[PDB]
Amino acid sequence: SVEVEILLNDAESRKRAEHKTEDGKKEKYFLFYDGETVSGKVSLSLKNPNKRLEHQGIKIEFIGQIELYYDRGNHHEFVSLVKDLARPGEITQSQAFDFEFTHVEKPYESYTGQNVKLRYFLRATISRRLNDVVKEMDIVVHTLSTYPELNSSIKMEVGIEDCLHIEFEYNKSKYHLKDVIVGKIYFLLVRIKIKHMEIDIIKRETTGTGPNVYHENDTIAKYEIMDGAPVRGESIPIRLFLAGYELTPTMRDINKKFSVRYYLNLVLIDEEERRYFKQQEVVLWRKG
């Protein structure tokens, strides 16, 4: 009876970002940053141009909220702005209503995770006696940072006295999202017979919900290094292209509800099928 659209000013020109939604599917959403004005109009179209629409008011909201999958009915809005667009009355005619929210606070980057989602959206509501007409439209927020940062390489060792000394050296402890992890694996001592080696990027998601803490992992990338036994004096250059990976910045204690942290995990498997692991955190940040 009423089709409601949310149309942003300069929709057709404004930046859109790809985002992996809850069912694994990728879509584009309008992209915003902290502080940016959110502007547009709410358009009502009447299915029958002759009939009047009785309502108890028309509203648009901008909302940022955290949705905890273990407590999914409980909304944890951290920013909510409300602009009433019409007092109760009557709509006899298809029309649009302008809106502008200025200085819009968006302190956290959008995130769709395993046990949590952090999302922003615009919600247009026509209040009715019977059933309200509600239309939402998601928007995506990114958070930029800047870091120093100078040439201080990091070392990751697997060391078994008298048996194994394998060293992975890489260029930074922090990387932006399209950066390259530049490193080298050195085989200093190889008395154990190794049959496979790889380096993985692991995302670890930590969520609090009620009195409980949930942990989930996701292997983002597997860089297969070598099959068969390495010998001492060999050296393998490593370049991991982060731009080919689906990545968010590191997120720590987001409104004390969740964390997203990233690790390099060096994996060796010997001829006896024994796993040897070693991990170090890398801080991922978004460069503007």
Image (spheres, rainbow, N blue to C red):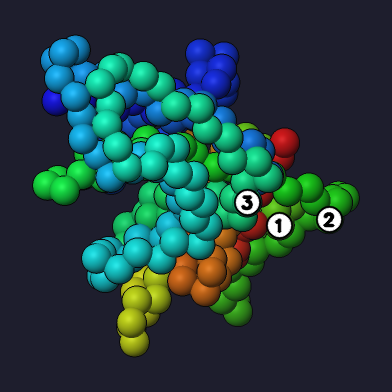
Q: As shown in the figure, which amino acid type bears the numbered disc 2? A: Ser
The answer to whether residue 227 is seen in the rendering is no
Of 214 and 90, the residue lying toward us: 90
Query: Toward which corner of the image does residue 137 lie, by quadrant?
Result: top left
Q: Nearer the viewer, mark 1 or mark 3?
A: 3
Q: Position of residue 35 (x, y in %)?
A: 68, 44
Q: As shown in the figure, which amino acid type bears the numbered disc 3? A: Glu
Kindly identify which numbered label has been placed on residue 152.
2
User: Is mark 1 in CB contact (under 8 Å) with mark 2?
Assistant: yes
Q: Position of residue 115 (x, y in %)?
A: 32, 62
Find the distance from the CA under tag 1 to the CA under tag 3: 30 Å
Q: Which residue is mark 1?
A: 173
- Kindly identify the residue that appears in the image at 55 percent across and 42 percent down: 141
User: Is mark 2 in CB contact (under 8 Å) with mark 3?
Assistant: no
User: Is mark 1 in CB contact (under 8 Å) with mark 3?
Assistant: no
Q: As shown in the figure, which amino acid type bears the numbered disc 1? A: Ser
Q: Secondary structure at mark 2?
A: loop
Kindly identify which numbered label has been placed on residue 132.
none
**Number of dots carrying numbers:** 3
- Kindly identify the residue that appears in the image at 59 percent across and 50 percent down: 106
Q: Which residue is mark 3?
A: 105
Of 140 and 76, the residue lying toward us: 76
The numbered mark, 1 or 3, whose residue comes first in the sequence reads 3
Q: Position of residue 275 (x, y in %)?
A: 38, 67
Find the distance from the CA under tag 2 to the CA under tag 3: 35 Å
Q: Secondary structure at mark 3?
A: loop
The numbered mark, 1 or 2, whose residue comes first in the sequence reads 2
- Kindly identify the residue that appears in the image at 21 percent across and 35 percent down: 54
Q: Quadrant of the C terminus?
A: top right
Of 172 and 10, the residue lying toward us: 10
